[PDB]
Length: 153
Length: 259
Ligand SMILES: [Zn+2]
Image (cartoon, rainbow over all chains, first blue to last red; front, top):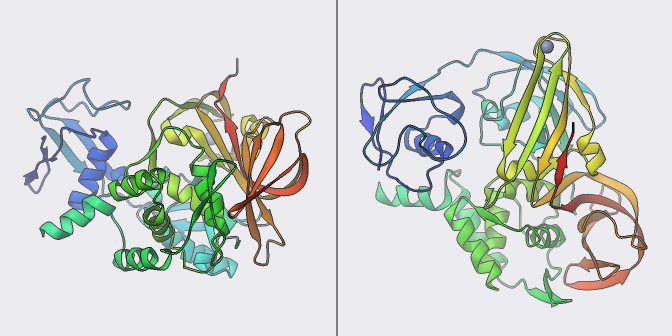
């Protein structure tokens, strides 16, 4: 049963020495404070070292008897990406990592003339989920997103 | 409040309609049956559910998966215990599927797997490079190392892929290491001639029948006993060779490196 500090400056505890995923921590943070994982900056209190990626958790922090700091990167500066369609046509879009996949789909549905729920998107082999933000998928300037028709069978 | 917190723990972050849709699907699919064919369970055809037969029979082949959403894992458990109604309604609900409406098995399959994790090891290593920006290796672990949407053969998976780099120049990435317990590749319906004189490298696949611009039909195929088994929504037949439009292809454990 940990705890995380912010700049509110208020705190709250992660109710879990369990599951343990940094990401679930993130998600725990995500659903506890409505903040997207990709904007979360974690650092062990007070050694500002900001963590490995592997498995929960220490390394350098474990048990109900420690604390970690959380700062939210509030950057959603616009960027240009590509969406390549059913026939292989890529068109540029202005986006923010903060917009949802669903929002980008509205754009694409706009420029392609296909109902937003009549197709779905992938990035580098992986499916993009509607409710999640573009930033979840490590989208970069000029990343290419693929449009797949929603078949009916 | 407490009640809202518990639903959040149970179903995770969902939209305001989710629980109503789930509970209605639960009631609506109550009559569906899972029937035993060649000693495995297949979803009996009903209300255009063939795409769910494909999805369900494919998931049943995926060893060591587990769902990170508790209601979904419980439903999954119940399904394995022979009571599939909850799991079916839940995946329809997470899939935004509508009862009696035809849908896309691959889109659903990978939507469902996005909520899952792998209870064993798996790893991809990709090499990316730009003439300007240089070289970086990208490591990927768990369930995500086991699925790919966009190609349907292992050689296409291992081929150099070209895209545009951050810097404006062209960028390349390519798989240089791969260890998995299985490998699911998915793509658009694609005509292949599948023969069993020589055992194919894959162990199962799904097939879309019909024109893709109209409402088609899904069949789930398994390679077994030197034959192709075709599970068509509750029934099964057997063939040696089959010219068909493949969608999802399931391969065995990968164990690959590139010098
Ligand atoms: Zn570059």
